[PDB]
Amino acid sequence: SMQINLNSTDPVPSKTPFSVSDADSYNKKGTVTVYDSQGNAHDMNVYFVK
Amino acid sequence: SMQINLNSTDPVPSKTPFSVSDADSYNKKGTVTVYDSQGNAHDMNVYFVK
């Protein structure tokens, strides 16, 4: 469970495609940490694109 | 009887042949002592490699 506040005045991203490598194809990137049954962790990145 | 708690995130050692002199040939080394008929103490080393 994660919350976000946003700005209504954010322009549309310029990068028409999307790639995790770039830093423009998305409005903003966050991440979350999760665990498996064996204990070792994983990280999920989330990208907001207007 | 000895309980050891191994780790999931232990990377594979580097030195492919097993050597007790190079610490990078095994993931972990543990020791124990046993006794004989004479009464002298003998130490065993057990080496864990993933």
Image (cartoon, coloured by chain):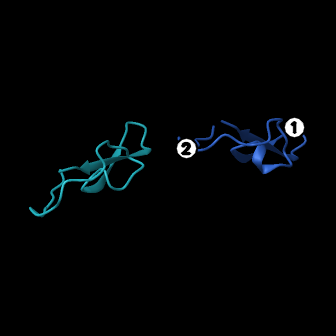
Chain colours: A cyan, B blue
Give the side of residue A40 with respect to residue B30, left or right.
left
Q: Position of residue A47 (x, y in %)?
A: 27, 49
The residue at the point 76 percent across, 48 percent down is B24
Give the side of residue B12 with respect to residue B40, left or right.
left
Q: Position of residue A39 (x, y in %)?
A: 42, 43
**Label 2, on which residue?**
B7
From what the image shows, is residue A41 above or below residue A28? above
The chain letter under disc 2 is B
Among numbered discs 2 and 1, the one appearing first in the sequence: 2
Distance of label 2 from label 1 (alpha carbons): 37 Å
Quadrant housing residue B1: top right
Question: Please, what is the three-letter code of the amino acid marked with disc 1?
Answer: Ser
The residue at the point 15 percent across, 56 percent down is A3
Other-residue count near label 2 (Cα within 10 Å), few / some / many at <14 / 14–19 / ≥20: few
Q: State the residue in front, B50 or A8.
A: A8
Q: Nearer the viewer, mark 2 or mark 1?
A: 2
- Could you say which disc has been placed on residue B37 in the image? 1
Q: Position of residue A48 (x, y in %)?
A: 22, 51
